[PDB]
Image (spheres, coloured by chain):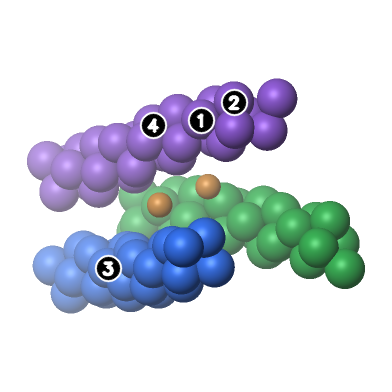
Chain colours: A blue, B purple, C green
Amino acid sequence: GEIAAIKQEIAAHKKEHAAIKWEIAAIKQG
Amino acid sequence: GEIAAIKQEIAAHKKEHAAIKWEIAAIKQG
Amino acid sequence: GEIAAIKQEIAAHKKEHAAIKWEIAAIKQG
Ligand SMILES: [Cu+2]
Ligand SMILES: [Cu+2]
Ligand SMILES: [Cu+2]
């Protein structure tokens, strides 16, 4: 339940990390 | 107490999400 | 253990906050 929903959370935070780095790269390659 | 301060936390993270999207938009409309 | 690893976490989130502000400043001073 809980430990799982924390893992589901680490999932989306890993994404969110990657997405912000991509958005920052793309601003610089614009 | 705890469940409340977690909700107080989801509050500020929602903001923080919006603020970063606004800062990224504004860089592109600059 | 837990309270400590939460504090270790607040550590890295403070950083992460500063790092994103620096990356945004530097895009604007580019
Ligand atoms: Cu993070
Ligand atoms: Cu987030
Ligand atoms: Cu944050």
Residue B4: image tag: 2
Residue that label 1 marks: B7
Query: Does residue A29 sit above or below B10 in this rendering?
Result: below
Residue at point 46%, 36% (across, down): B10
Residue at point 68%, 33% (across, down): B2
Amino acid type, mark 1? Lys
Mark 3: few/some/many CA within 10 Å (<14, 14-19, 20+)? few
Residue that label 4 marks: B15
Instruction: Have a look at marks 4 and 3 and say if they share a chain.
Output: no
Q: Position of residue A9 (x, y in %)?
A: 42, 63
Instruction: Have a look at marks 1 and 4 and say if they share a chain.
Output: yes
Mark 1 / mark 4, whichever is N-terminal:
1
Query: Does residue B24 sit above or below B1 in this rendering?
Result: below
The Cα–Cα distance between marks 1 and 2, rounded to whole angstroms, is: 5 Å
Q: Nearer the viewer, mark 1 or mark 4?
A: 1
Residue that label 3 marks: A19
Residue at point 54%, 68% (across, down): A3
For label 2, the SS is helix
